[PDB]
Image (cartoon, rainbow over all chains, first blue to last red; front, side, top):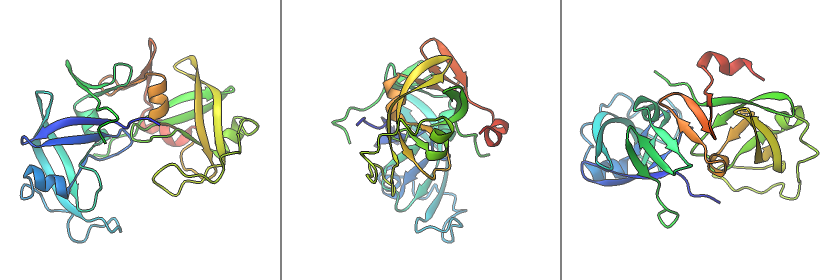
Length: 125
Length: 130
């Protein structure tokens, strides 16, 4: 078995191990990490309360923009916040395309422009 | 906006198939219909039927330990599970993305393996290739 794709980044200087998933239409951060980072009233509540997706999972709202630090590179980031999502942050196919990112597995990093951000080892779950 | 999801075309035993490129999927998986369509049932080892390794309720028809897949004009050895009713013909997971040291280049919209880039299929190509 292989280690899934995780990358380290600070969000308002709060380190998050983001899970990079090219099979996700949307980028998403759970409420617990949204609480830890400090972004709980930047939310644009347009999908809360009666979330029309018929699940248990409630959508807190939508952070339109907050800066993310990938090894010194600062990027405008956008994503959804959900209450009972088990992972800190999802880097969706949206952000992966918008910032024209490259999932490199021969060199094993997420390459953005000239900034290579290695993937985390197995000892880091 | 909702972005196009990532698919590449390829062939297994002369037969044309489109493959979903999922960096969050730990396993490569092919539906029963496709392997039947590609003549791969005889290769399906049925010793591991009824197991589940994933998140979901996963119940496989078996595992294909090696089949040649012509991706990027190169013959590339794949291994994947076979599961009867899966919406998607073929999923390229993180096992094979890593096994063949692939590159998912969303700047120039292509899948790079060796010196060859397969461009991701355009949105209007997805729901017509079988």
